[PDB]
Amino acid sequence: MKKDPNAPKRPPSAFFLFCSEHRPKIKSEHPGLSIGDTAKKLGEMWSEQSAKDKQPYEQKAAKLKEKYEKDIAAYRAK
């Protein structure tokens, strides 16, 4: 709503990565499956993922959320 094309992307969350990559897969075996049922299943696998699909996902959103607090400010009206 109050974001621009030059502004930085919102702060991604670890569960948002894992789900963001497994979102188009749950819609293939479930046509019409909204983002609630697949979000309930994914969260079950996300909390079950080991370092293969969980370590590089939290270190990409955790280090991007804290940097957004200074990025958004500097881009707000420095």
Image (cartoon, rainbow, N blue to C red):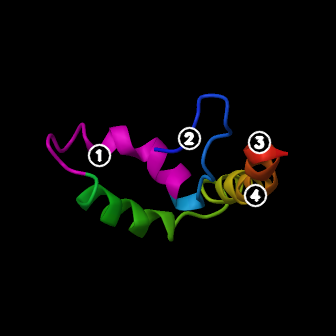
Amino acid, disc 2? Lys
Of the two numbered discs 4 and 3 on the same chain, state the one appearing first in sequence.
4
Near-viewer residue (45 or 7): 7
Badge 2 marks a residue whose secondary structure is loop
Q: Say if the magenta span includes residue 33.
A: yes
Q: Which residue is mark 2?
A: 3
| Residue 34 horizontal/vertical position (percent) | 21, 50
Left or right, 32 with respect to 37, comes to left
The magenta stretch spans which residues? 16-34
Label 4: how many Cα within 10 Å (few below 14, some 14–19, many 20+): few
Task: Kindly report the distance in space between the C-alpha atoms of the residues bearing marks 3 and 1.
Answer: 37 Å
Of the two numbered discs 1 and 2 on the same chain, state the one appearing first in sequence.
2
Q: Which residue is mark 4?
A: 69
Residue that extends furthest to the left in the rendered view of this protein: 32
Amino acid, disc 3? Tyr
In the rendered view, tell whether residue 26 sits above or below residue 52.
above
In the rendered view, tell whether residue 12 sits above or below residue 4.
below
Near-viewer residue (32 or 8): 8
Label 1: how many Cα within 10 Å (few below 14, some 14–19, many 20+): some
Badge 4 marks a residue whose secondary structure is helix
Q: Which residue is mark 1?
A: 26
